[PDB]
Image (cartoon, rainbow, N blue to C red; front, side, top):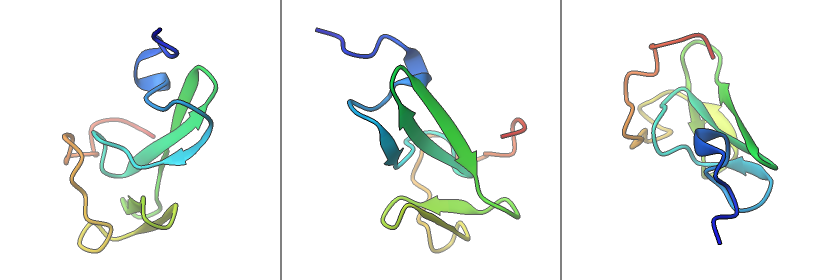
Length: 73
């Protein structure tokens, strides 16, 4: 049924904050056919387990994209 077809802007099935599988500083914010990422302060990683942020040594960054320093949020 493909309920997304929006690309990285719809990696979820509903709406809300979710764990990113690629970026490491900006997590995935699911919003309709749009997934706005959110980079933490001081190049921090988002704690998908708490919908918050935290160093990359505690937030466990396992996203395919470890080098989040590739663009500007």
